[PDB]
Amino acid sequence: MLLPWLILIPFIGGFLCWQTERFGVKVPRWIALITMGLTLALSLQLWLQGGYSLTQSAGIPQWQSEFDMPWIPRFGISIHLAIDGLSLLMVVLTGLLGVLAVLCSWKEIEKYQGFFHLNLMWILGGVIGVFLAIDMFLFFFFWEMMLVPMYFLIALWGHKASDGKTRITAATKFFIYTQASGLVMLIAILALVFVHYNATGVWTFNYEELLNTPMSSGVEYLLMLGFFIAFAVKMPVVPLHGWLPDAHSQAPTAGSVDLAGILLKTAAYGLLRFSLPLFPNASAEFAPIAMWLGVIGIFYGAWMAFAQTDIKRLIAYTSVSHMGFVLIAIYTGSQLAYQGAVIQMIAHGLSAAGLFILCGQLYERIHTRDMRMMGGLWSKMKWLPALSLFFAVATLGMPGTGNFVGEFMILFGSFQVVPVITVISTFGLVFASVYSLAMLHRAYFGKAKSQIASQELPGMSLRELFMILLLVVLLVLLGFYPQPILDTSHSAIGNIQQWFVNSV
Amino acid sequence: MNMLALTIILPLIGFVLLAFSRGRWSENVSAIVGVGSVGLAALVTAFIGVDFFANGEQTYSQPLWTWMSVGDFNIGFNLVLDGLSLTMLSVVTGVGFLIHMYASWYMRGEEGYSRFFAYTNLFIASMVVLVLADNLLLMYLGWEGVGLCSYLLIGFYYTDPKNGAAAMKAFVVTRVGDVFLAFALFILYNELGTLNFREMVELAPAHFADGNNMLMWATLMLLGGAVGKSAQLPLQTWLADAMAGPTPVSALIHAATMVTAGVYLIARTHGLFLMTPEVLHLVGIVGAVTLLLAGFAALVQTDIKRVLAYSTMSQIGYMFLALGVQAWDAAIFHLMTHAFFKALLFLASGSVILACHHEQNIFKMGGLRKSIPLVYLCFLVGGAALSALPLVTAGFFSKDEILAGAMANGHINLMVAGLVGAFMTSLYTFRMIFIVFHGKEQIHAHAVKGVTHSLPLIVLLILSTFVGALIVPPLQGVLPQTTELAHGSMLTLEITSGVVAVVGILLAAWLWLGKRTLVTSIANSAPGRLLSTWWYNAWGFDWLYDKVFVKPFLGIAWLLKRDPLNSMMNIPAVLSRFAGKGLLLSENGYLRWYVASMSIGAVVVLALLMVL
């Protein structure tokens, strides 16, 4: 019921901001803040009003709210929006990140600003629609239309048409690397539906009847690779992640909040929801390749993070290290491991968003991007580097932050299922420390005479500090007290694991 | 009595105030609030200590809230205040109180003031969490909590990068130990399910009827965690470099706070180490080989702070032996004495290096008895206890008891190790003060007089002596494995240690009382410098631990300066663009070849139809 409205407010707000662009220029900032407030209101209403602590073994079909509507009846394509417990965590996270995106874009007036915000709400609404998606075509359409408006963001707002490096390399690799694999998973969807159409005799694009379709061995394996390729180019996996640092280092850091904190979520959401239950034996065969790619991703991202000299590419290469833990979590037979991935995933978004906001904040203070050029700014800034120290501290497994409990319950479940690949995996924490300290010492520890421009520094406004203070206190409560959201996700995680166990 | 969290909240909350009053407060109010947090901690500790005496040595547990709970994974914020943990709390909330009270006077006059009293409170708070935790998880929060605080205090002076660069080697090395520590934590949950210490104690033999082979992996890798955090051979790197920070943080790190975490983990899991005897004796094996390493490196270099540091390494491993010889209460008795002397020994050295005014040398000063005898009596008291002198010393009872226990274990190599350690402690006891305080004063050390440090000096003077040895720590509340006692040979071993100490003290005094030309000759002899260079490398261990992984790590980073796999999956675009350029060049514009294209399409279509 609430789901059609909850995916449509982003699109309605873009229309109204661009409508009132003719009326005024200070309107869309204040319009956008209220519209994202309504998005979190409906999302938090579903958290509180709904039975978040529901039955742990109520089957694979279980939803607090559900919407159905005929869209293309010839294939049974329907607007099958349906919200689960873990999907509701995703919706509340993106509503909060949308508030941060529209708050960081405050006091940013240009030649056109309504165009920026209709695009801003369009891309955030696309991610919400992926998170509420049970029909395969609706899932794919939303997956691919959140991908078009970021291209305009990197192009027309990466820099205003002055340098050609903001389109022809950064934005173009971002677009092609995702869309080729999106078309791969579309033909994977179609091969799965056609083998189901031979089995039963109805053209259906719905998840519940495609869940248990009879397929011979050696056939569903190729479709599982087809799903995983599109789910491995969106979250950074080892062979195909070259788009991520270019995308984050060129887009404005509000666009980078969208590009890191929430676009990385949807691929592991799809690995939990759409790839694991549909292909149980194929995923059981593919598991060790996934573990090898996971350990390679953690070690690889940390080394590339240590070796880099700038900051946006630095945090962009932390992200590929973080997601390796999540991939190994998903491809195991443990309930605790999956519940560790969820808390690690929410904390991943919350620990990347603050760093990107602050890295963009530091650049507009000093007008210099290279990290090794500055140094010793602690005597000049009064609140930026202290808050930045805790966010770099929250990146690695420091307890009292959500990242520690996240990565570390994965390791418990991972050692429960398989010893040797887990005992390799744990060493990324040592490597997490070295790139964390490298960031901290090269940027803030030292003498302010490392740069001439490090001798005249501005002040920090109240609202940026307010939205940084909220994230640090929110992230500490998730580290100390993670029970409420684990009780929320228990049943959804449990039935996925029980199906992955029982179907093999 | 429902006041355990006040030993954590009151310090920790004070840190938050000093983390946001980034120098905007004045000197006095910042100084009072920084000392008062730790002062309230000691007072609440004393109340629960005297109530623990009123409890009849009965443990008191308090769960605040469950941390995380999955249906097979139950972790809670459980605090256990038993006899072993009360003693380890007593050391911290007294020593940190005394060290931090000195810092109220030492820190003033320079910037970074509110910053330093912020991170000290966090450092103390992390150490209290480790020794009161009831679950191995919450205790893990203690381990890397105090590690990050050592990073924030070793690299406290961020201006020059030597001490600003020395902290990360400790940070890397302590997290290697923490990976080793968490490995055993995974294995214990896989094997025995619950991580609570007591429930683990009477769950371990129930689950282990059939298979035992994998418990040695748990316990050996658990041991690898304990050793690394404080000091030991496989990971002895950072304690020389940890001296690059200020004097009070070196005392806190090296004396009794952070280095007393690896002792608490072996002692708390003593029944768990009793489940396997060979992993328990292996602690003493590694302890016996580190007393042979950690001693004479104090003699080698001319840095006073490196002197006090190699002595701490020697003493911590001396404990590992004491725990390996199944003498648990005696080892904590050694700790109870050891905290008192080391902290003062470190602190007094700081007062004189304030008076030295940038000397940092042991060979260019002399005749310091006439400058100020207060620091003279400070080193003197510390030296006597360390050397195992029988004259009104505090720690000699602890050495006598553990060697009695060690010979009750019956390992002649361990008494040989103990005998050479007593001789080696007496060697570097008075050699430092004889080479520094005796001679001629060509550079005057301007002594500073003030009651603000004299009163804690008197308190530390009256505490580090044998008056402090009369305070028996609470050890009857845990009922550990009983430290066995020997009579008749106790007097024989006592006089043997006294003779060994006296011979070492007389040899140092004979090194002093000679011309020192033979000392100069052995400091100039080529085999002497070879051994000095060999033990500059410290059995090549820092040499080996740099050149085994560091330059391979820098080499693979230099090979990863440009990202390979992003480039090697760009070759579809490279092949497509180059093949597209070739197809564009295939077009001509001359219309004869267009019609030839039409004929050559007809030819291939007919050929492709005739092969079907």
Image (tube, coloured by chain):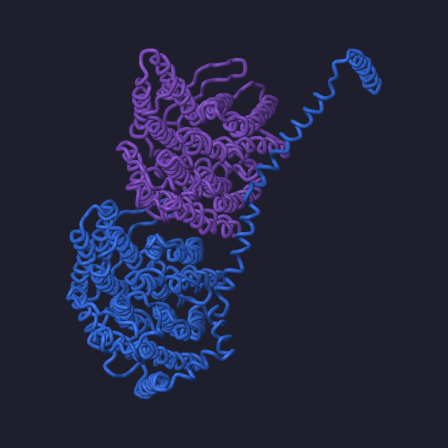
Chain colours: A purple, B blue
Figure quadrant of the C terminus of chain A: top right
Figure quadrant of the N terminus of chain A: top left
Picture quadrant where residue B384 is located: bottom left
Picture quadrant where residue B484 is located: bottom left
In the depicted view, which residue is nearer to us: B446 or B51? B446
Residue B380 in the image: state x and y as whole percent: 26, 77
In the depicted view, which residue is nearer to us: B137 or B390? B390
Picture residue at 24% right of the left edge, 44% below the top:
B20
Residue B255 in the image: state x and y as whole percent: 31, 66
> In the shown orientation, is residue B570 left or right of residue A487?
right
> In the shown orientation, is residue B558 left or right of residue A442?
right
Tell me: residue B457, above or below residue B507.
Answer: above
Picture residue at 42% right of the left edge, 59% below the top:
B207
Residue B468 in the image: state x and y as whole percent: 21, 73
The answer, for residue A466, to whether it is visible in the render is yes
The answer, for residue B191, to whether it is visible in the render is no
